[PDB]
Length: 156
Image (cartoon, rainbow, N blue to C red):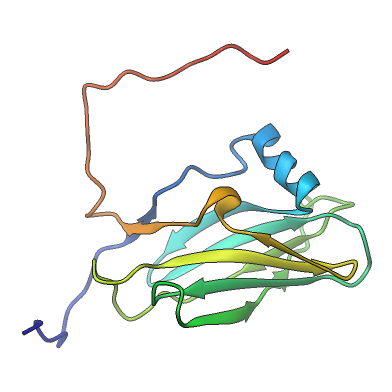
């Protein structure tokens, strides 16, 4: 039935959500209430990259990204690395992560990931600072024009 996967190159993928960092407030709120929040997550060739933030509550810190390709059935705990740059916050540390996308990805299975920060004898779980990090392809995303931008007042 299904067409074999012998020789084929799928276009790059995109994100179905707006970067978290974008909103300093809506962002810090998660890093202050959950003590953890993803800064930015870029996409690369059959691979991804992103840096997660954490509160300097304790010394020992454990950051691991949880990703799955089977409607949250088969996930793998990937160890995060540490970044040392001028930009990186002095107090709050900055851990990075590099996950390798699966061979292929079709519209027959779901794919989402979440952040898992362990500290102070606790386990903070940040799943797309809302529901889940829905990752879709770039060719799937539909383009809709003739739309007006939204804008509102600044909370006092």
